[PDB]
Length: 276
Length: 272
Ligand SMILES: Nc1ncnc2c1ncn2[C@@H]1O[C@H](CSSCc2cccc([N+](=O)[O-])c2)[C@@H](O)[C@H]1O
Ligand SMILES: Nc1ncnc2c1ncn2[C@@H]1O[C@H](CSSCc2cccc([N+](=O)[O-])c2)[C@@H](O)[C@H]1O
Image (cartoon, rainbow over all chains, first blue to last red):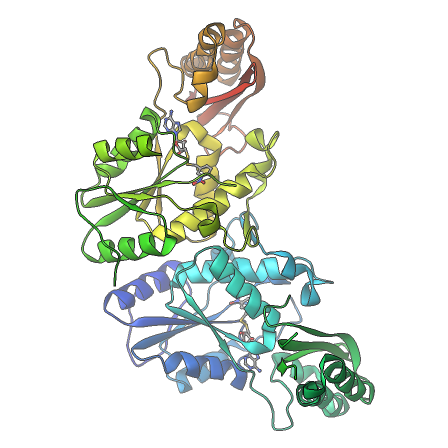
């Protein structure tokens, strides 16, 4: 497969991107991987820009809607995605087919640890097995020096660090802070599914979290009650969970995580919390 | 700084990071890294794996010795001209206990997975780890554990691992008995009866010109002629351990208990 530096090169075949990545590493370029499900927004572009700033980097952005972590409802805009990558000066997009990634269906897979059964995994007990299986595959195909994930999906980031540690993967996991709208709303491809009213109410998630982070000088109870009060004051926000955990998602430094529904649209957000 | 490596000597590393660093450094110097996973207690069967790895031009041979949850073994490797032994502790391999693991496909529940339903999840997890630590160009496994070999091929294909899996033919005693450290536990009567596994398989392989049923019936007759041999299974499958096709290549696998000693063997079969 051909590779043209300073241009966007799109490969669909795992063998092609593997070959190009290997070649590029051999010539001294450091391979950065940004796994995505497409429908790219500024949150994804922050990942790309973090990748870019690593000197000598070549940036691979994968776009794959992984059926195993689910599907028909997921936003798909491939045209726009590659345009954005071109604008960002990304040199490699990897856009594999389902058949190329899963020629044998679900055969060997990744079994995450107990964290996958909790929070996002509570009602979706196979979700993270899906995510970790695909991320492992992407990591083996691309063999990046570093792989970039958003903090917005904090439990996912934690589990990917677990995958990496547990399987001795020779990749550094880089967590990138959540990119937010002007009012604080965490950027998400799911935000498009909010009407004007729901969009207005949705600010309560980030407002609750930031209120909690500042309340936290008064202790964990204060922080949680501050967040709960903001969410309770929000018209038509239905809370699935609001949980304060250790940073590894098992007191002093923690992470406060929220998941809520606005209509049918389920939103997530989380924030660093320092107690005292 | 990259850990010390002395060419032509047995270099022993216990730290995963150390062997990772040396393997990476060596491959950059134009060596091809060969991995031979073992559980120690080495015999000629394991040496055959080592010798296969050694004959690859440019090879550096990494033999791991690890029991999934010594000086004699090292002497044998030294004598084989192996340059790297990797001897990690359980704590070094599992610093966070069992957390993320590999879930094999359904083949792992069959055959050997009958009595041991989680056995292969353990093997694939540790093999995946060793692969990621050492990043070998090729990894060597004996055909004696054929189902394990097939499952490792599935692991490598399924997770897109960039390693060649090399199956090495089973090394046998003079009478055909597959070499295994367990053979030592057999008393004379049991050791004599144990020959029936290999004899049954080789009979089947030659009977196979007359078809699959002839091959199975020949093997069963041989096993039926042996006292104190409790057959756990005797199965003819295709080479990937799916159902046997009407003709073509297959594999015949047997497992049996002699007292408390469980023995396995298997053989290539060509049907008709
Ligand atoms: N507002 C935001 N700010 C920062 N990062 C954000 C973000 N919104 C999303 N992201 C970040 O953009 C990425 C979204 S997809 S990457 C995870 C994944 C899961 C399953 C399958 C596959 N896959 O097939 O490659 C990949 C996440 O890293 C998210 O945390
Ligand atoms: N007679 C024989 N002939 C050829 N190969 C033989 C053999 N006897 C044994 N072997 C071969 O010697 C190797 C034995 S150990 S490698 C598999 C394993 C299992 C569990 C845990 C771990 N682990 O913690 O790294 C590794 C196999 O490749 C076997 O097929």
